[PDB]
Amino acid sequence: RQQLQVLARYLKMDLDNGERKFLKEKDTVAELQAQLDYLNAELGEFFVN
Amino acid sequence: LEEITKDHKVLARQQLQVLARYLKMDLDNGERKFLKEKDTVAELQAQLDYLNAELGEFFVN
Amino acid sequence: LEEITKDHKVLA
Amino acid sequence: RQQLQVLARYLKMDLDNGERKFLKEKDTVAELQAQLDYLNAELGEFFVN
């Protein structure tokens, strides 16, 4: 693991770049899902569908 | 010039791959999860966009 | 020039 | 073994070059030995020796 880290650093590879992007999008999903949930609570399923 | 450093980075990348495989590290796991969530975002954003087109901004806000 | 050999010695 | 292979490839070392040359010569030996065997079958040992 330490050898892989040293090589990652030589190569200027951000190993966590993808898990970092993932957690930003997971927050965007929860923000959009809250907006949708709110509109469902205001209009109801029958209306929204 | 830069061909020697290119060939060294190829070796280093190959050594990193071999170690990733020994360690059972999926290096692309995070970029793969990211692209699934980016599709979930676009699906939710389409639902919201649709409700905005039906009710209008004045009403939704 | 010598920056590439420097970066290789850092790795080593 | 995988690290040795990566280095072999960086160095442009054909690790199997010698086993490959060996198997070509082993075929040359069998071809020459067949020619000799054939002459022995035609002339006999007494004559050939």
Image (cartoon, coloured by chain):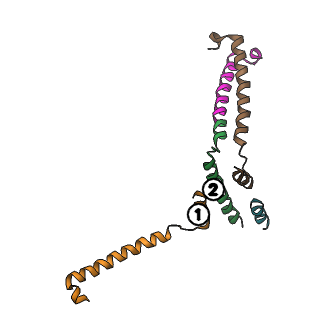
Chain colours: A brown, B green, C cyan, D orange
Q: Chain of mark 1?
A: D
Q: Which residue is mark 2?
A: B14
Q: Secondary structure at mark 2?
A: helix
How many residues crowd around disc 1 within 10 Å: few (fewer than 14), some, or many (20 or more)? few
For the point 63% across and 39% down, which residue is it?
B32
- Label 1 vs label 2: CA separation? 10 Å
Q: Are marks 1 and 2 in contact (CB under 8 Å)?
A: yes
Secondary structure found at label 1 = helix
Could you tell me the amino acid type at mark 1? Arg
Q: Position of residue D23 (x, y in %)?
A: 41, 70
Q: Residue at x 69, y 41 (%)?
A: A18
Q: Which of the numbered marks, if any, corresponds to residue D9?
A: 1
Vertically, is D6 above or below A18? below
Considering the whole magenta stretch, tell me its main secondary structure: helix
The foreground one among D32 and B56 is D32
Labels in figure, total: 2
Report the residue at 71% width, 32% height from top: A25
Residue B40: within the magenta? Answer: yes
Amino acid type indicated by mark 2: Gln
Residue at x 57% of width, y 68% of height? D13
The range drawn in magenta is B35-61
Compared with D43, B51 (above or below) is above
Quarter of the figure that contains the C terminus of chain A: top right
Please determine whether, in this image, residue D21 is positioned above or below residue D49: above
In-image side of A25 versus A49 (left or right)? right
